[PDB]
Length: 207
Image (cartoon, rainbow, N blue to C red; front, side, top):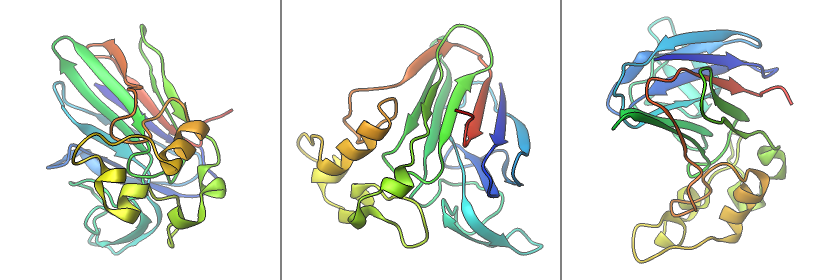
């Protein structure tokens, strides 16, 4: 599958692509404003994620640190990133279908559109100014807006035991971005696409 990752933000972002135990394609790339990166994602990739990282620096060996979304200090991500991270999530060729979503469960850093570039299903977007409107307890010191599980680390917010419900914090994300997951047990906003679709992830999508 082809994924085009496009940075339309005014700021640089360091794109990342991983399935949690390995990079997808090169795993990461610096994208200055307006730049894009086209990757190949292998068919059958399950539990893949693409995200932006902000305010990074790296040395010539590709080791360094990002203020949002850092993946073990690497340019070329193999593992998932540190919250807060707006997440483009996908599982491909799963019993004939692809499944895509945007999630705010791990917070929000950069606005995102995640759309097919082939026919037959909708895209989703979360492009409200969540960072500017972020409630005080959720503001991350390095920038972006943490989820309440990261901040409070209890099942009330983390949905590890019993049956968690919405909180004022989850409702904040949901109100600003109805089409993204706001907590683990939110009513799903996943889109079913034809198997073997192609996609575009756009940071700071055009309104």
